[PDB]
Image (cartoon, coloured by chain):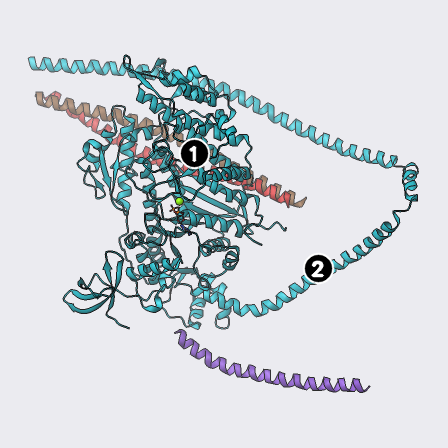
Chain colours: A purple, B cyan, C red, D brown
Amino acid sequence: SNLEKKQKKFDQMLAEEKNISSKYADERDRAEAEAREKETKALSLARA
Amino acid sequence: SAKKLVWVPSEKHGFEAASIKEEKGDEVTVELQENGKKVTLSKDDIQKMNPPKFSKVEDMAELTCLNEASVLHNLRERYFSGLIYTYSGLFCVVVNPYKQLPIYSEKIIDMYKGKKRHEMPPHIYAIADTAYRSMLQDREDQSILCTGESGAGKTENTKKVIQYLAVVASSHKGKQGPSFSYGELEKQLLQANPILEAFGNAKTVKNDNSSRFGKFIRINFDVTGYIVGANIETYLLEKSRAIRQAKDERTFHIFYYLIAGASEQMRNDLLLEGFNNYTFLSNGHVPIPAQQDDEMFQETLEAMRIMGFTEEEQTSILRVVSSVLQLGNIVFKKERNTDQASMPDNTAAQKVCHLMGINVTDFTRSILTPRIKVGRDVVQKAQTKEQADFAIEALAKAKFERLFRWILTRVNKALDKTKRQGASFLGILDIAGFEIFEINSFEQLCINYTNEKLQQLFNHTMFILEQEEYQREGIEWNFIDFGLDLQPCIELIERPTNPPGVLALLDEECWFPKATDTSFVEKLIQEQGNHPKFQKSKQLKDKTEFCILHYAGKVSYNASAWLTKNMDPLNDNVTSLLNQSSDKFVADLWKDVDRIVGLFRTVGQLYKEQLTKLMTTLRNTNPNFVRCIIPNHEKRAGKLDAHLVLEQLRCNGVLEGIRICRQGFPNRIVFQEFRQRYEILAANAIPKGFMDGKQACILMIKALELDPNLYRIGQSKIFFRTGVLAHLEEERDLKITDVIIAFQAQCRGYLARKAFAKRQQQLTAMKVIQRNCAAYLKLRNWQWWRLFTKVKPLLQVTRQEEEMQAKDEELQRTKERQQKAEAELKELEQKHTQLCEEKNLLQEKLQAETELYAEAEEMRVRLAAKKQELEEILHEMEARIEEEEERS
Amino acid sequence: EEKRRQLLKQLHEHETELEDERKQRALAAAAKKKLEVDVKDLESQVDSVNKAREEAIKQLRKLQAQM
Amino acid sequence: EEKRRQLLKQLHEHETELEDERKQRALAAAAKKKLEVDVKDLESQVDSVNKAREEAIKQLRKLQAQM
Ligand SMILES: Nc1ncnc2c1ncn2[C@@H]1O[C@H](COP(=O)(O)OP(=O)(O)O)[C@@H](O)[C@H]1O
Ligand SMILES: [Mg+2]
């Protein structure tokens, strides 16, 4: 019974883990874009 | 795996591993794996092997197949490993190692406290903590119960439990290691054990530290769950042995500790000598391993000092204990011309009466030829050598009982500073174990009886209570009885109804002055004859021997002088003298004399009274058992007798108990509680509208998709199999932990902000302090300050108006207090005169009723005499009428 | 808080002392009912014994008259 | 002051309520003792009645044997 409940749970959890992984990839790319933006800002401040 | 492998019985090891070759009818041919020896057993004899994965496995409830031999082997391997603890479902079993191990520390205590059994290895700390947590959560009373034979180790478990309690239950004063400064009551509690042990324990063939007494501790808690008080109850002790010592056995440890440890100054004060100088000390000095008598003497006295004893109330105990030791030296010799006792060694009596502060002349004659009041007359008692011996030994018993009573009351009164309020309590029961030797008198029987009666109580609570609960809730279950029952043996001894048991017969034949111990045993044999648990004399009828059946084996008893134990006879003249002793301490010990007996209450009935009370407490509280097992009778570490542990395990009924634990449903909860505790798991499925909560519970149980064999639904309680609720609770809490951490960060943030804000006020205060102190410190070496200091008190501050105003203000307060004191005085005066008049009226009325009673009772006696007279005359008339009728 | 502790201790002690008196009331009532049953039983015994006595006297007088 | 008033009121009310229970204990004990005396009296009646019955039977048998 426990194994069957787990089997059902693993299927759901793998799909949700893919969603979470995708969310982290999006936030990673957002943080990378932020890093580029603030790097540009730092260069502008240095030139100023 | 090789399915032909089996446990086969062994004369040396109880059971041992072997391999089946073939089978024939009801039998199997097998080869022992240790030597290759062939043998044939019955198919009922051999048992199935414990697989490798289950070797040394923890809880007995987890075993793939319940086998006595597998349990035995797991126990032996664990004893060789030194892991003494093993779980058995709801309870725990242990085994005496006879050797100290580092299984106990503050680090371990902190590691165990508040954790669940499933996440931890076994320990007594876990049992103590579980009882504490359940006590706190349910707000009911709880108890811990250690059980086993005389050598089995209980006192080590008890020592660990009260130590654990004395740290976990402590309230924090707001002020880390084992030298931590505990609270005052915990400090007393941790000293009470060594105090009581010194006065109450002795060496026996079974145990070098054998407790001669039964005890019960309890600790009381507030609504917050912290300790606020404690009590120490103690039951009747094996006091007889102390001056009638069997070979290689010892008296109470305090005697040896005093005789060895006393300074020359102390020795002269107490009029003491070294060993072998005392008639009451058979075998002379008897040694004991591991102890250091002088050092023990120091530490027990220091323990009494920590318990807040004065030096006088220590030395007074030493005086009385010296007195019982010395009085044995009052040797008697009988005058053949008169059969009366005489005392050639009157020096001993002079020493004793000096230590007691009474008259030597009266002390001598009240022992040798006393004058005793018998009703109306006061008459010279003829007194033999044996009667004089009996009198002084009985006096020693009386002195000892009074001193032990004083000790027990004094130690409780230390705790009795605390208030009468409390929420609930946790108990600790520690009764002396099963015990036997070359003589079996009444003094051992009561202890052995309570040991087996406790096992019978366990039978009820473990087996019967379950069937009753399941039947009450009406669930799908089937009754079973494995036949664990001691009741006929209890009924043989006790008298709740007829026919009369051992105790009742002993009391009845004790009361009758014409009867003796032979009369008692004869009546027992006649009236109990062929009772399933009784057995007659082993041909030695002249020895007045008889026997009774117990689960620990049949025991033969010796009835000699049981009547004096029930009657408790004591000398009235010496009692009167001691009651009026010159020593205030002795006068206090002997203040009560209403149990004087020159021939009241039966010791059996007294014992029953305390027993029913404690047993009712055991029925009301929730007990936690911790069973301890004897490895061998030679008091040796590492060595283990398979047959001893086997038969102890069997009679404890653990193989039967664990079966019903796994087969039944140990967890149980009311439906409303089940829903309110776990609803989060099915909140979308459970309807909001009001209904029978069991429907919501069914919906939740279905959502969890539980197997219907794992639970049973009653009308009120839902029963569940082991631990499921505690794992669901863990999962539910884990679901909440994420938001809890976020809230915790906010609360800790608030706390940090508060602390920082306070620190700012402290910083600004400190800055102005520093300005002031630096300014003064720089300048105070200037000379002018001395002149300023001379001049200022002549000029500044008028003072006297402020002083006058202050005096006037305080005068008003003092006048107010006076008015209140006078009002209270008047109230007390009004109540005083009322109580005085009521006292007067009651005294007058009492005197009237006493006179009326006297008048009634004297005439009652007169009428009884006339009744007897008329009855005798009527007998004479009946004789006469017969003589007439025969003549006619 | 000290006033609370004192008054609560007083309340607790006074309550438990009189609760023991209430237990004594329960015991007294039980004993009363037991003795009431004993009185009824003994009254039935007196009824039967007196009837038997009177019947014995009747038979005695009858036989005495027949002799 | 309000805590004092409340706790004192509670103490007073609970004390008088349980004092009424103590009076009920006194009444119950009085009734118990009364019924105990009645039991002893009735036991004495049974003693006398039974003795009289047995004596009547003895005399009956004696006279029956004499006839
Ligand atoms: N848990 C334990 N750890 C260490 N030694 C133990 C332990 N339990 C028992 N012992 C040993 O067993 C001896 C006797 O056990 P004891 O507690 O006196 O048993 P009982 O109270 O049943 O007579 C002790 O002196 C000690 O050496
Ligand atoms: Mg012990």
Q: Amino acid at mark 2?
A: Ala
**Residue visible at 59% across and 85% down in the picture:** A25
Q: Does residue A14 appear to the left or right of C29 in the view shown?
A: right
Q: Are marks 1 and 2 on the same chain?
A: yes
Near-viewer residue (D11 or B497): B497
Q: Does residue B98 appear to the left or right of D22 in the view shown?
A: left
Per the rendering, the mark at residue B243 is none
Upstream in the sequence, badge 1 or badge 2?
1
Q: Secondary structure at mark 2?
A: helix
Packing grade of label 1 (10 A; few <14, some 14-19, many >=20) is many
To which chain does the residue with label 1 belong?
A: B
Q: Amino acid at mark 1?
A: Phe
**Count of numbered circles in the view:** 2
Measure the alpha-carbon separation of dots 1 and 2: 60 Å
Asked if B42 appears above or below B222 in the picture, the reply is below
Near-viewer residue (B268 or B150): B268
The residue to which callout 1 is attached is B255
* Residue D31, x across and y down, in percent: 41, 32
